[PDB]
Amino acid sequence: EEWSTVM
Amino acid sequence: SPRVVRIVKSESGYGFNVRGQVSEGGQLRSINGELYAPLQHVSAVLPGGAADRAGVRKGDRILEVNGVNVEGATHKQVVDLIRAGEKELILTVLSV
């Protein structure tokens, strides 16, 4: 389970 | 080799995406032949954004955020560390 977040 | 980059937010935030596991720890995997626990990585770099201008590249693995070791870290830990400063971010990254 991977998440991607905009920084 | 690992290197340190300093990034100051622009209009557009820092201009990168971070991707990786939700959990803590897990299966070891080498990066450039060096053994590590799972590492979050840079999944996107906004052209012309702050991260791009600091030399961050797609695929860079994140070893430290703001001087804190994030080997094996959860995604939340890394996101929260990136958010620690109001405008400045220091990363230790490893390009692949």
Image (cartoon, rainbow, N blue to C red):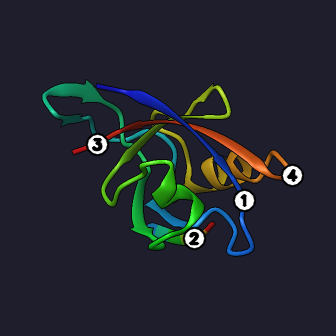
Answer yes or no: is residue B21 visible.
no
Label 2 packing within 10 angstroms: few (<14), some (14-19), many (20+) = some
Same chain for mark 4 and mark 3? The answer is: yes
Q: Amino acid at mark 2?
A: Thr
| Local secondary structure at mark 2 | strand
Q: Which residue is label 3 attached to?
A: B95
Residue wearing tag 4: B86
Which badge, 1 or 3, comes first in the chain's sequence?
Answer: 1
Q: Is residue B50 left or right of residue B62?
A: right
Which residue is located at x 81 percent, y 52 percent? B87
Reading the chain from its start, which is encountered first: label 4 or label 3?
4
Label 4: chain?
B
Q: Residue furthest right?
A: B86
Disc 4 versus disc 1: nearer the observer: 1
Which residue is under mark 2? A5
| Quadrant where the C terminus of chain B is found in the figure | top left
Residue B67 placement (x, y as % from top left): 65, 26
Tell me the amino acid under the disc marked 4. Glu
Mark 1, residue position = B9
Dot in front, 4 or 2: 4
Considering the numbered disc 4 on the image, is that residue within a helix, a strand or a loop? Answer: loop
Report the front residue among B3 and B68.
B3
Q: Residue B75 at x, y = what percent? A: 56, 55
Q: Image height check: is B79 above or below B4? A: below
